[PDB]
Image: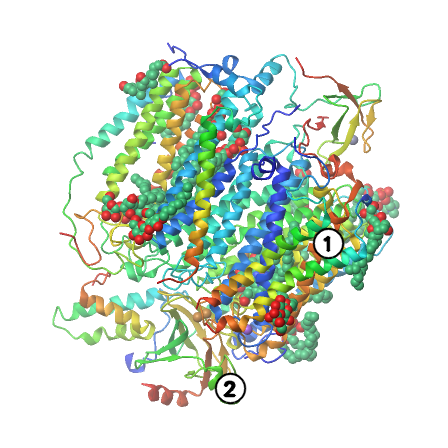
Amino acid sequence: ASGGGVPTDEEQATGLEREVMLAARKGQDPYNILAPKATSGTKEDPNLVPSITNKRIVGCICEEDNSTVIWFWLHKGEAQRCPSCGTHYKLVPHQLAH
Amino acid sequence: MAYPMQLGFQDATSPIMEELLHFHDHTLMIVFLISSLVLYIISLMLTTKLTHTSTMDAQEVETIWTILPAIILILIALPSLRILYMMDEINNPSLTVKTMGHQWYWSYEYTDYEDLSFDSYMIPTSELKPGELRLLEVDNRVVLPMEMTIRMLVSSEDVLHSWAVPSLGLKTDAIPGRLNQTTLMSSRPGLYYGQCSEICGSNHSFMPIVLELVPLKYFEKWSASML
Amino acid sequence: FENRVAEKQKLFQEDNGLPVHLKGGATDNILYRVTMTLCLGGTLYSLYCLGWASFPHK
Amino acid sequence: ITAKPAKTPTSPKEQAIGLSVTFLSFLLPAGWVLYHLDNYKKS
Amino acid sequence: HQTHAYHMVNPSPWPLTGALSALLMTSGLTMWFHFNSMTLLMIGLTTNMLTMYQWWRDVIRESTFQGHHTPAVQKGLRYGMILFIISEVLFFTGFFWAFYHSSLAPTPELGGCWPPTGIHPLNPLEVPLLNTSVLLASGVSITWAHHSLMEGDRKHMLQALFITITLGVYFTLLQASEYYEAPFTISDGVYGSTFFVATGFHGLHVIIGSTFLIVCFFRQLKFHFTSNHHFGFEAAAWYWHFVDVVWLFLYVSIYWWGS
Amino acid sequence: HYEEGPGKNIPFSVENKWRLLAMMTLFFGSGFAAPFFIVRHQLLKK
Amino acid sequence: KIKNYQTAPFDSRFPNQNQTRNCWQNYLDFHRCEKAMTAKGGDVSVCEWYRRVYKSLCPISWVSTWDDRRAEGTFPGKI
Amino acid sequence: ASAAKGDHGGTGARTWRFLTFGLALPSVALCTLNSWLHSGHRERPAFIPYHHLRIRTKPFSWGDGNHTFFHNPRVNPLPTGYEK
Amino acid sequence: MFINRWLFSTNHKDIGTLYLLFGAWAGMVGTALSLLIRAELGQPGTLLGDDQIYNVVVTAHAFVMIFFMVMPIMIGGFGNWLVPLMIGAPDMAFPRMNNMSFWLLPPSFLLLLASSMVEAGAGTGWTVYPPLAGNLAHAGASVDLTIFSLHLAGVSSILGAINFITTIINMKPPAMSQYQTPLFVWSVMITAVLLLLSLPVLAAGITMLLTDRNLNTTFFDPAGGGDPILYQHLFWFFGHPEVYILILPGFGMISHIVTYYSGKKEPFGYMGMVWAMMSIGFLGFIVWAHHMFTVGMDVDTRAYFTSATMIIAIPTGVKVFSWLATLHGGNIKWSPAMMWALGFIFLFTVGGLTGIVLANSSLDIVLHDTYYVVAHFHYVLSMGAVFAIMGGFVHWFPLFSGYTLNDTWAKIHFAIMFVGVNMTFFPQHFLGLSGMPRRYSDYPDAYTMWNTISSMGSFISLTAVMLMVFIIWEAFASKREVLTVDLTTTNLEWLNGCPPPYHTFEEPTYVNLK
Ligand SMILES: CCCCCCCCCCCCCCCCCC(=O)OCC(COC(=O)CCCCCCCCCCCCCCCCC)OC(=O)CCCCCCCCCCCCCCCCC
Ligand code: HEA
Ligand code: HEA
Ligand SMILES: CCCCC/C=C\C/C=C/C/C=C/C/C=C\CCCC(=O)O[C@H](COC(=O)CCCCCCCCCCCCCCCCC)COP(=O)(O)OCCN
Ligand SMILES: CCCCC/C=C/C/C=C/CCCCCCCC(=O)O[C@H](COC(=O)CCCCCCCCCCCCCCC)COP(=O)(O)OCC[N+](C)(C)C
Ligand SMILES: CCCCCC/C=C\CCCCCCCCCC(=O)O[C@H](COC(=O)CCCCCCCCCCCCCCC)COP(=O)(O)OC[C@@H](O)CO
Ligand SMILES: CCCCCC/C=C\CCCCCCCCCC(=O)O[C@H](COC(=O)CCCCCCCCCCCCCCC)COP(=O)(O)OC[C@@H](O)CO
Ligand SMILES: CCCCCC/C=C\CCCCCCCCCC(=O)O[C@H](COC(=O)CCCCCCCCCCCCCCC)COP(=O)(O)OC[C@@H](O)CO
Ligand SMILES: CCCCCCCCCCO[C@H]1O[C@H](CO)[C@@H](O[C@H]2O[C@H](CO)[C@@H](O)[C@H](O)[C@@H]2O)[C@H](O)[C@H]1O
Ligand SMILES: CCCCCCCCCCO[C@H]1O[C@H](CO)[C@@H](O[C@H]2O[C@H](CO)[C@@H](O)[C@H](O)[C@@H]2O)[C@H](O)[C@H]1O
Ligand SMILES: CCCCCCCCCCO[C@H]1O[C@H](CO)[C@@H](O[C@H]2O[C@H](CO)[C@@H](O)[C@H](O)[C@@H]2O)[C@H](O)[C@H]1O
Ligand SMILES: CCCCCCCCCCO[C@H]1O[C@H](CO)[C@@H](O[C@H]2O[C@H](CO)[C@@H](O)[C@H](O)[C@@H]2O)[C@H](O)[C@H]1O
Ligand SMILES: C[C@H](CCC(=O)O)[C@H]1CC[C@H]2[C@@H]3[C@H](O)C[C@@H]4C[C@H](O)CC[C@]4(C)[C@H]3C[C@H](O)[C@]12C
Ligand SMILES: C[C@H](CCC(=O)O)[C@H]1CC[C@H]2[C@@H]3[C@H](O)C[C@@H]4C[C@H](O)CC[C@]4(C)[C@H]3C[C@H](O)[C@]12C
Ligand code: CUA
Ligand SMILES: [Cu+2]
Ligand SMILES: [Mg+2]
Ligand code: NA
Ligand SMILES: [O-]
Ligand SMILES: [Zn+2]
């Protein structure tokens, strides 16, 4: 037998390391470790951008392998289109209190 | 030696050094070109109002930009490597002088036949005879017979020096415990000057070389007059 | 021995706004201030050394 | 690059000072070492 | 509030105390070499150990207690420790080079031959063989420890780690006896020079090595490490294997082919 | 939290431009003065 | 051969600008060839060739120093 | 290789323990048997004042400054010969 | 707070600022040392005294401009400022370690300044070659203090490289591949691998020199079987890689500036510029013996190094021809910083060829240890690496500060500096052809005119350096606040306002996988 005596992450993980381990298991990425998956990016089906504030900077790789990310500020409001390819993006405020 | 306002190389006293001048002349033809094509094309791009800020395609122009310079570079190397192997070559030398570098003078050994050895210091500005070249003149010259293949072995009994005679196309480092071989061929007689080409301390500036080339028969006497 | 990793965790997450290197109480400060004394102390010394070694002697 | 106006505009006269002071801060001490050079050697 | 998974580090005094520790240690050695005094050097050395202690204390505080080492932070720690081992590698390379320059072309001054005239090399089948055996054992022992830890056998991980460190201590004592018995010194030109400086720097790397495992052994005592988050023991293992392969290269290069 | 914005993110003060000129005078000037006073001291020994 | 000796020829064994071993090997080849020729009751004037070479290429001080060490018993090369 | 045993895909911590106690430490015992015999004060070398050994370009920063750090009077001559 | 903000920092920006300040101060000392040099050569005869005191000044000039000016600004200043903002990272992998890399640099300098005030200083050259650098010619603490400067200065660099590489590799947006990071970002990553791999071998070499001076080793002493040349190899094994370190980030900035001020949305041939520097990096490691062509090494070797040294021209060409294509159909905005970049492109290409000359073992026979060499590497360093620095500095000064400079003044600065370095160095081509050696306080009568002229140039370059201290003041004096910046859509650094907040990317950028 082992005896054990080695604690496990489930038991001894605390702080942010825990919050990631617990969030990951429920299928959520609150701390932005995975890359979001893209939509059609039309006005009807825009790219939803979860934020903790009234703006967040989006980067747009307009086509695969493109050397240049298009960056701009995204605001609460109507959807916004990339000034390169006209792909649509929409801000989705929430929070992380309790 | 070097004269006022001089732009380019000392005049070739040995054929190797000649070979360099013409090779150097080749390499500068191309330098003068690439520098003008780059200065020209720069000005071309800046002297139009017409514009094109949308994405541009590489592959096909980046081909010219590599295959040309690779040819331009074989063209330079092909002769550079000829002249480098030409400096080695199975030559047949008739005289073997060893030079030693000291803080801060040069000693000479001609030891083929006899045990002839002597030092070679600089003439202090205060003691030059009117006509004598400041920082260049030595009390005892390196008399060598002209128009013959000579083997010079270089080493130092202290710090690093460099044994250096521009006009003949010679420079070899003095490395303590190391006997470095070069070969010396004057096409002409006369006086042929050089300086220490490694930083050796307080008087690096002030430890020059002067060859005196003369006939074989004016040499053998000079040899015998020094023992 | 027995696991006391959970006590030391609560001590270090406590919102007292002490930076990590003082969050252990009393000792950390005595180790901090003792450390900084010798560094700035031996720095001053080492200048005087440089300073002495610059001039000729005897 | 668009900027505001200056909050504390540095008039010519003020510029002329800063230029005067800055040139002297380099020039003056260098001068005093280079002028007393002869004196340092007689030792 | 942050929504990235990285570490924002509190303002630390220790970079300053370390930097200062260096000015003390280097003006200190200079003060020992030239004015033949160790005042400054002991001041430097002490500040350094106090800086090293406190710094890595806070790293554990930050990881074990505050849980700041998220899967990201911990994957930057690997990239870090590995680029470090590269830098140690290129340093040791510099010494092998010094060796291979001097043995492969001996000078008139030595006899024109390797080994030099007057040098009585150690037999590589004697204590050096026994040194080589101890280390390779301790890569069998630490690899046990890792598997014990991963399987959650606290006990067999302490036994495995204890065997590793005791071998390390046993390598060190063996090595310091072999320095003493050596019929040649660091002064015995370029044989002694290569031999001491290179087998020497390696030796301090084993003491660094055993120090870092002893930390691991006390930290495991206090239950710091899980089945799955034990980077401080990975860093130590890798470093230990590096310290072993370097030895192997020394043994084959300096002891055997240069005997 | 530390001060944000223009003239706040430096370890000197730009609040008054004539103290600032004195500060840049020393900083840059000291550094340029240094080699000269160092060459002096090397000649002033022997 | 030695009647027309000017200086040392090219040695196909030493083709490179570094000739430290040339001076070295021809000095061994004398002092071994000489220990050889006085330990069998022969003529030393066979060993002359290597004496000339080693002197044509070897610096004075280097011979100076190896001589003082053959005498002092501190010459590291086997003879 | 000059080595042959046979894969034991059976458990981790157990196999590397097997290997530790079975192979690794036995090596260190054999290797010790083989040194605790072959290691013994072998005859010390006759002194020759060879100029490429016992370098002193600058005194050491300790002792009388003519003794190395792990200097052993029995086997380690000085520049001027052995110590009594 | 102040002690917590500036002494104790873990802010990638606040640390960049510390370096820009250190490297600015270093430059002041570097300049003085360079003026002294040309005081001594500006007329025949002797001014200070013998080659000794002269070469302590020459040597010091080299270590300060290289180790305390160009690497500290370029890598630690612009690295620590721009790198994290170009990849939307909140700071550096190892921010505590980042600060020790800074504070290790005052010490490092002070051991250098100590060396020049102890005994007769270490006039050895920046190569520090035994046996001159050894304990018989340079007996004393000087050369030991110089070896210790470099130890600390190499620990700063190697720790700082571990930080960048771990930052650029690990801390991008997940969606972002390496192939969508800016050129600067790439330049710094590559420049950190060169540091990481070369500085350890530099350290190893200067360690054997300490133990030859102090512990009676004979690594470089023929008395104990050693070889002075061994040292030349280990040092130059570092020393070629050291110079592609000093230009690579200049490539970076130059790719940035020429792009932003041509109004283009990316530079021409992105992946071309990636292949180029990864090549220049790689071939920069296999060329070190081109510094040793008069040491007396086998002909077959000398011809490899000739040929290998020249291959570097192809990938460097690609970069010259790219920048030039990045201008092609640009909307050229004639800023100071464009002027700095343009000058780079032509005076780098001058210096770059003058070193293809040097590649030929043949010529280097005659050109070795002449001013021709000094001329080559003052066109690539004084008229490249410093042009990148002034270019960048001019373009990004408002991001760090939040204020504008006076653009007229800043072209007046460019104007005078151009005339000064070209008059300083263009004559040094002629001197070394006429065979004037390096590292001489005094010269044969013949060489006077060019040496007069060369030094006049060095007095124009001083007016430049003094003007730039008064131009930095004006801007802070005046406090004109940046309002709006162009081309932000392709230049993420400018997106958080001039200057950006203590904490940037507190909430990371959104980049999605298509
Ligand atoms: C203010 C700074 C000072 C400038 C110096 C000017 C000099 C003025 C003095 C009197 C001047 C008389 C001659 C003018 C030519 C001067 C330089 C030249 O071409 O000299 C040729 C050679 C040396 O060759 C010789 O062997 C000289 C032979 C000359 C024969 C011509 C006929 C006789 C007239 C010349 C008298 C000497 C003849 C006797 C000698 C016979 C053989 C030696 O020099 C070299 O190798 C120099 C290496 C530099 C390479 C850099 C690449 C180019 C950068 C810029 C390119 C684009 C332009 C934009 C340009 C913009 C960027 C700069
Ligand atoms: C930033 C600094 C820097 C840079 C970028 C360079 C770039 C180069 N250097 Fe130089 N160098 C130094 C700094 C630098 N160097 C220093 C400090 C020393 C001396 C150390 C000392 O001794 O004190 C030195 C010394 C030095 C020597 C030794 C000389 C001697 O001691 O006698 C040699 C020999 O090969 C050399 C070669 C090169 C080459 C081939 C390049 C290449 O990288 C240049 C390539 C670029 C171009 C050629 C222009 C762009 C290309 C094109 C436009 C393509 C078309 C070209 C052709 C068809 C040929 N350098
Ligand atoms: C980066 C390296 C660098 C730089 C910039 C310089 C700049 C200059 N150098 Fe130097 N030099 C060397 C590195 C450098 N040099 C090296 C490595 C050697 C060989 C050393 C040896 O032989 O051992 C050498 C040798 C050397 C010699 C030969 C010594 C000899 O053989 O006797 C001479 C002679 O005139 C000389 C002159 C100058 C001059 C006039 C400048 C001027 O062009 C400089 C003008 C002033 C500046 C360019 C100041 C810039 C300051 C800033 C940009 C800071 C501001 C920034 C901020 C506020 C952010 N140099
Ligand atoms: C079992 C191994 C024991 C480990 C060593 C323990 C204590 C002292 C050494 C500390 C570790 C550092 C080693 C590096 C320096 C030199 C190699 C030392 C190897 C050694 O220990 O050398 C001994 C001599 O030591 C001597 O001189 C005295 C040596 C003391 C001088 C200190 C060295 C100072 C220089 C350090 C340079 C710092 C470089 C760091 C670079 C940082 C990264 C770039 C050898 O014994 P010996 O009597 O000559 O001959 C045997 C005769 N029976
Ligand atoms: C060593 C020195 C050697 C120098 C090298 C010289 C190169 C020779 C090239 C010459 C051709 C000039 C091309 C550059 C001008 C821009 C061309 C352009 O604007 O072309 C567009 C490029 O955009 C697209 O497709 C996208 C693809 C872009 C393709 C065009 C750009 C290629 C060239 C750019 C490189 C400039 C470098 C110059 C400075 C070094 C394409 O538009 P269309 O298909 O509708 O055109 C149709 C026009 N017809 C009917 C008259 C043919
Ligand atoms: C021969 C030796 C003598 C020296 C030669 C002169 C040197 C240089 C002086 C350059 C004069 C200014 C240059 C013209 C434009 C740039 C700077 C300027 O004049 O300052 C403007 C102030 O405006 C305004 O007139 C508002 C009022 C303030 C005016 C500012 C300038 C007045 C003083 C200039 C003269 C200085 C004298 C120096 C003598 C040592 C602001 O800049 P803008 O023009 O709005 O645009 C810049 C953009 O970045 C902003 O979006
Ligand atoms: C003259 C003086 C010579 C030197 C004498 C001795 C010096 C040093 C002793 C050896 C070094 C020991 C370092 C121990 C650091 C302990 C902290 C630690 O190990 O920290 C770990 C991170 O690793 C990390 O930063 C990585 C830590 C890596 C440390 C690097 C060690 C090598 C550096 C030594 C310096 C070499 C100098 C060169 C020699 C000439 C923390 O993460 P975990 O452990 O996974 O925690 C997770 C769980 O707790 C909860 O789930
Ligand atoms: C003779 C005298 C000459 C002078 C020599 C002495 C010089 C310096 C001595 C001071 C060094 C001791 C102080 C401890 C430093 C530990 C740094 C460290 O270990 O840093 C870690 C990362 O480095 C990693 O793993 C990867 C990197 C680990 C390297 C460990 C430190 C190296 C120090 C020696 C460098 C020698 C160079 C070797 C090559 C020649 C952690 O990064 P931090 O930002 O700290 O925190 C981030 C938090 O997320 C952690 O929870
Ligand atoms: C608060 C933190 C900062 C603390 C700084 C204050 C320390 C002041 C200490 C005074 O210095 C002493 O240092 C050495 C003590 O060992 C002596 O060296 C001596 O050591 C050798 C013997 O070990 C002798 O041979 C030499 O003569 C040499 O002078 C030295 O005489 C003595 O002045
Ligand atoms: C290369 C870097 C710098 C180059 C350009 C420097 C030009 C120097 C600027 C003036 O600096 C000097 O000016 C005076 C000389 O003109 C010196 O006065 C000296 O001479 C006066 C009279 O000759 C005395 O009365 C003074 O006290 C003093 O001794 C003064 O002390 C010194 O600062
Ligand atoms: C040169 C120095 C001498 C020491 C050498 C150190 C070699 C490095 C080995 C690291 O361990 C890895 O490889 C083992 C061997 O392939 C695996 O063992 C075991 O792991 C499996 C499951 O964990 C078991 O099923 C198997 O029996 C297997 O032996 C183990 O998993 C894996 O971590
Ligand atoms: C990179 C890391 C740097 C590592 C630094 C290592 C420091 C080394 C310690 C120096 O040791 C000293 O110890 C004693 C002073 O405390 C003295 O010993 C004396 O006592 C010995 C007895 O052990 C005798 O052999 C001699 O008489 C000797 O002088 C002597 O001054 C010196 O040996
Ligand atoms: C395949 C690779 C990367 C492009 C991409 O994957 O996006 C590209 C980019 C840079 C290219 C190289 C450079 O453009 C330089 C050379 C250009 C020549 O026309 C072909 C070979 C040449 C050596 C190129 C080979 C290949 O086409 C490279 C290496
Ligand atoms: C203290 C602890 C018992 C309590 C626990 O399991 O935490 C035990 C577990 C394993 C033990 C160690 C291991 O058994 C390995 C060593 C065995 C030696 O015979 C005694 C010391 C030795 C170093 C032990 C010390 C101590 O008794 C340890 C560390
Ligand atoms: Cu002898 Cu320079
Ligand atoms: Cu190079
Ligand atoms: Mg040289
Ligand atoms: Na002069
Ligand atoms: O170079
Ligand atoms: Zn888009």
Is E85 above or below relative to E104? above
Q: Position of residue E113 (x, y in %)?
A: 28, 56
Q: Are marks 1 and 2 on the same chain?
A: no
Which amino acid type is shown beneath numbered disc 2?
Glu
Q: Between residue I293 and residue D31, name the one nearer to us.
A: D31
Residue I101 drawn at (x, y percent)? 53, 42
* C44 left or right, relative to E39: right
Label annotation for residue B132:
2
Q: Report if the CB atoms under discs 1 and 2 are less than 8 Å apart.
A: no
Residue at the image position 80 percent from the left and 30 percent from the top: A82
Visible in this render: residue I454? no
Give ligand 7's quarter of the image.
Answer: top left
Nearer the observer, B86 or C34:
C34
Left or right, E86 with reference to E213: right
- What chain does badge 1 belong to? I
Badge 2 element: loop
Q: Which mark is residue I507?
A: none
Q: CA distance from mark 1 to mark 2?
A: 52 Å
**Above or below, comparing residue H74 to residue I494 in the picture:** below
Q: How is the image coloured?
A: rainbow
Residue E12 lies left or right of residue E141; in this view the side is right
State the residue lying farthest toward the right: B49
Which mark's residue is nearer the viewer, 1 or 2?
A: 1
Residue lying at 32% horizontally and 79% vertically, measured from the top left: G5
Residue G10, picture quadrant: bottom left
Q: Amino acid at mark 1?
A: Ile
Tell me the quarter of the picture where residue I12 sits: top right
The location of residue I198, given as percent across then percent down, is 50, 47
**Residue at 46% over, 39% down:** C37
Residue that label 1 marks = I471
Indicate whether I393 appears above or below E7. below
